[PDB]
Image 1: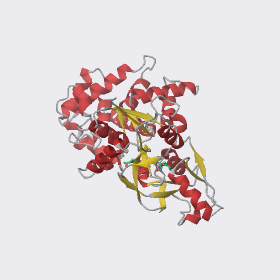
Image 2: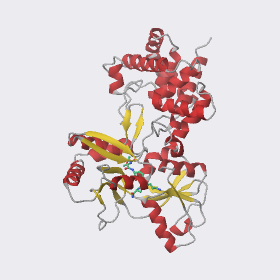
Image 3: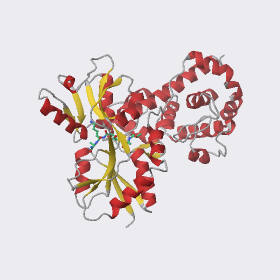
Image 4: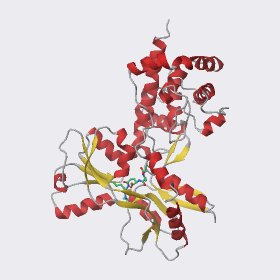
Length: 418
Ligand SMILES: C[C@H](NC(=O)[C@@H](C)O)C(=O)N[C@H](CCC(=O)NC(CCCC[NH3+])C(=O)N[C@H](C)C(N)=O)C(=O)O
């Protein structure tokens, strides 16, 4: 009897696969709960919001939905909502360099898009009784990340989303901006079907209450909010510079790992630079640490017993990069093979293989970096990642990682001639 089925959205704010496996706010909260129940967690992902509620309410479907949901009516007993675990405020979003709307009326005449079946579509439905001139579009083939992208690039003028979605994604869409809060703050909650037995619901709320206080929720809220992921290019002045101040402390370790693994030490050093700017005490709330930013797991798998030791960190991250490169399909030849190895280092081999399958179906060459790097940002677009085996990944940040490591590599190559 020991298997909790939880239905969710495949999206960065809820549940997704990265290079280490499953992750996401909802995914963890649901995992720390199935642990507290002594059962196996089975994640199931819905096609869109209507379908989530449909699967929740058909027999015999999933136990609960954990998916950043805004509770509906309390006197509707068909669906029942847990206590709230996170507070958000819906926000109108516009693009920088356009007329910032200041109040609900200003939405008339703009192109507006929201997820179909959402809290946020209902808010506009309501607003449209008060202003029949309002027009807006609804879609099941987008996620909140698509909407922000569409605003960012100017394919639509405005959207409406929860503020936590904005905290999560803002950094990856430089052109987007809050126009105004549009509704009162409210708390998200898990959704269970109604309703005759309260066994589960009572356990859910005991958990969500214990997780606040005990800090668990604020723990999570901070790991994921505002977080950067892949560092920006620092420019020639700063690299300058760290070449002078930092590299000489570590060059010998890069050179020795280079010999040991029969590979260009300058590319190892470039990775290290993108990962930590050559700082052996660097860390993230995401659980990587050291000069090459290894996870505990990857560190153990590579013989690394102290992640804060530069020589060990450099030895293990390099081993990891080189093994990833060796495991790629034989049809990928150098120099592309190294660029694919960097892409997998960041996004994981599974997402990378989906991008290669996608490229093929597009009539492109799946052994060429210039082709597959065109596919990678589509893994952030629902229309595309829903047709893939591993779903969403922030593929545009993978591309940025590879480009940045190649820029540092090219400079290092230049100052190390002839
Ligand atoms: C906590 C977690 N996300 C986070 O980033 C963490 C860091 O805070 C989360 O649960 N997020 C969801 C994200 C996406 C979302 O906006 N989902 C919708 C659908 C999007 C509609 C926008 N056009 C919703 O709010 N509510 C559903 C529709 C509902 N009321 O049933 C949420 O805030 O909701």
